Length: 162
Ligand SMILES: [Cl-]
Ligand SMILES: [Cl-]
Image (cartoon, rainbow, N blue to C red; front, side):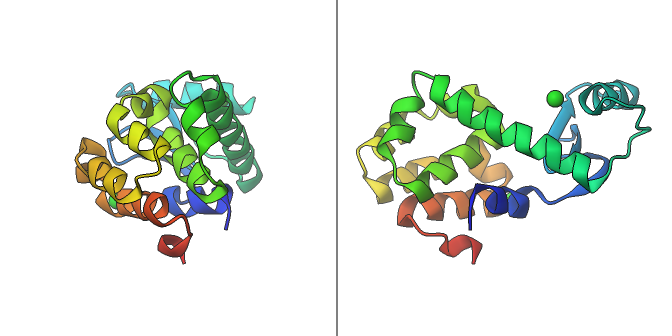
């Protein structure tokens, strides 16, 4: 198991524009297109991202390409974030994947706000962090995915994905 496989499981794969759990237009493997309520706006962001007139549909290769870019960007965003970096640097490989997952889903700023959880993770107080992570809108809105990521931080194994 790895970050790619992990996110592919959490996000799924869709080749036509769709609405995410928050109602935002998305495509591929969780690639958010726009928050605007307009489908045309989403189509235009899609064409711009792909480099062609897609008409709201992309191929598998194209989805994978967006996915590679998104993963790379999340990593680099963590590495650039003063609040995230030190956490990421302190963790083992499996738990780093859990942090990347959360940034991919919620954005760097979003994650940077779990101040308290971040502090516990850095301190390696696993059970405590798991408990604090659960007291969040994130956990209440997407509980199954959240539970998977949380178990990963708690245990440091990929069991929730097996
Ligand atoms: Cl893009
Ligand atoms: Cl869920």
